[PDB]
Image (cartoon, coloured by chain):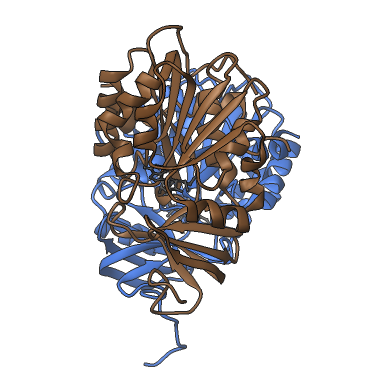
Chain colours: A brown, B blue
Amino acid sequence: KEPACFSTVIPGWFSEMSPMWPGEAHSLKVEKVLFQGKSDYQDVIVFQSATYGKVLVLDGVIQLTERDECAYQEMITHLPLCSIPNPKKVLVIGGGDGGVLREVARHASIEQIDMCEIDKMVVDVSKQFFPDVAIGYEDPRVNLVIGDGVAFLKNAAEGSYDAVIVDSSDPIGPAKELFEKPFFQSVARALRPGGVVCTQAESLWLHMDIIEDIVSNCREIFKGSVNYAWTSVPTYPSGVIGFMLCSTEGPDVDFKHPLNPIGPLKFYNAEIHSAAFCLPSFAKKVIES
Amino acid sequence: SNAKKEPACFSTVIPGWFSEMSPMWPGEAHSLKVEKVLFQGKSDYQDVIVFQSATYGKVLVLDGVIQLTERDECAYQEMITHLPLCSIPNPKKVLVIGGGDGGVLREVARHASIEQIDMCEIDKMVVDVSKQFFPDVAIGYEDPRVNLVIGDGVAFLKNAAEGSYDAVIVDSSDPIGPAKELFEKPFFQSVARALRPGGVVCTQAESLWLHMDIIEDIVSNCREIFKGSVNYAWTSVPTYPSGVIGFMLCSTEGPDVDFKHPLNPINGPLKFYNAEIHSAAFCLPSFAKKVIES
Ligand SMILES: C[S@@H](CCCN)C[C@H]1O[C@@H](n2cnc3c(N)ncnc32)[C@H](O)[C@@H]1O
Ligand SMILES: C[S@@H](CCCN)C[C@H]1O[C@@H](n2cnc3c(N)ncnc32)[C@H](O)[C@@H]1O
Ligand SMILES: [NH3+]C1CCCCC1
Ligand SMILES: [NH3+]C1CCCCC1
């Protein structure tokens, strides 16, 4: 126990505390802290955990563990790219571990992977400590930009992207404006007609108010399809994460029935793609109202 | 009276917080902030805790493991009940094993066709504390169709008439403790015997992220026993280890049972279950699907 998010009661325990999920915390046994640093944007920790392999933490929040990252990486990537024909040019906002790069690379149709990550410290420790995730960076198709995805999207050419994937941290910290309407509007402008967005869109158990405004906002902006998907990620709070899938008006996009089917994938397949749009009654009624 | 020292259960990792520990999920714990510890008791089977959480309402704990929070209980009780009951026509006779919180009882009651709900819970203390501290519970013990027995469900199944149940739901605690043999081949054989032809069992069958060795053993055993359908489904439960849990669905030799396409549609309205997510619960991640249908 060295970092302030580590136990005052016993050595070698990390607990994920945050006002974003009050009264609850996922606690993980720590074999060793591998890195602590303060970047320009974030407090950054990597630790070797007993049972989840290596762990990336940003401002006290678990961004990734080796044991379960296939769930988030595969779903956030293949939900959008398997939903459209022949994707060629794709933009990753955040994605500092390079996991999304690794999944995007699986698509042979892809010619260009642009990535805009605000925090070089995250890139640094990701290539050093998680090479099986950060292998993403090695694909000759990748262009890596260190910068705020807000500004990058503003300077993107209108109608230039087949897909945008917003692999962002939580609304507390530098990803704050990535959750807000003007950022969604710049995504829309930068997408071809029938082009798609896939965002990190929180917990239906923990964040329904937030998700309800994101969806209302996306319905004002994207006149194609607007859909919400969820997945299991044990080491995210509540055990689940969700995604906004949105298309700009034009060629029809059916996110629930992928027409572009893709080591072997460890999580994603064509059936769980459609199953992730099958929300629980309490959520479904909100999401589609 | 003094007795044998029992370790601290509360504030083991964060002062004011319960952390859920077990060798069934090594090197991790779900932690919940504690407002008030309502009950601590030792029965003839288990350590029994009830506490008021800060953000998950009341929480039942058995042998240090969370069994239920008020906030997320709708996911397990709706799925483990309607996945089986919505897969067979006009169920009349249903057996619940364990289920001492009475949640399953409640979701079983939503079914008009049902005429008797047999229940066998080994631990009278869990019944008593669930009725005391939890709001829907004592009422959803009062449905005239409920026949509650205190006993080991292994014994109850050996007592049952051959082919006498349309459906059995095993709402059990983990293999460590009194539920051990509900996971084992002989109890499964005895469920298949108690079921009619085309009859259905739904079992609490752990986490695909945590328990794949265990799950492959249950599935392989079920395939040997139940010559109908054998299918594994999963759902989201935040306060269960890894935040998912699963269910073995099996039907015996008889009228075909399609657990994936439920022929039967269905505590106020359902909060969680719906026809679409019935189907979605059988769509497993690739690493699980290989092991489970191989
Ligand atoms: C690490 S990734 C989440 C883990 C699951 N792939 C989220 C990244 O978002 C970055 N981030 C946050 N805000 C921004 C903005 N505004 N722009 C770019 N990148 C951002 C942050 O530095 C993380 O590395
Ligand atoms: C509380 S319930 C699970 C929580 C979500 N409904 C699980 C119950 O199984 C009982 N249980 C455990 N072992 C057995 C046996 N062997 N027989 C019957 N009931 C059992 C145990 O006492 C709990 O009340
Ligand atoms: N808790 C958040 C951290 C980033 C990815 C998942 C959401
Ligand atoms: N860990 C288990 C305890 C209660 C039953 C389902 C999950």
Q: Who's the residue at 73% across and 38% down the image?
A: A263
Q: Is residue A143 above or below residue B255?
A: below
Q: Which image quarter holds the C terminus of chain B?
A: top right
- Residue B181 placement (x, y as % from top left): 63, 56
Q: Residue furthest bottom?
A: B2
Q: Position of residue A128 (x, y in %)?
A: 62, 58
Q: Residue furthest top?
A: A251
Q: Is residue B69 left or right of residue A234?
A: left
Q: How many numbered marks have been drawn onto this rendered protein structure?
A: 0
Q: Quadrant of residue B284?
A: top right
Can residue A181 be seen in this snapshot?
yes
Taking A102 as reference, is A87 above or below it? above
- Tell me which residue sits at (41%, 36%) in the image: A242
A232 or A221, which lies in front?
A: A221
Residue closer to the observer: A265 or A289:
A265
A286, B188: nearer the viewer: A286
List x then y, in percent, for residue B119. Answer: 44, 46
Left or right, B253 with reference to A51: right
Asked if residue B184 can be seen in this view, the reply is no
Q: Residue at x 32, y 34 (%)?
A: B271
Viewer-side residue, A103 vs B26:
A103
Left or right: residue A70 versus residue A59 is: right
Q: Determine which quarter of the picture holds residue A59.
A: bottom left
Q: Residue at x 46, y 18 (%)?
A: A160
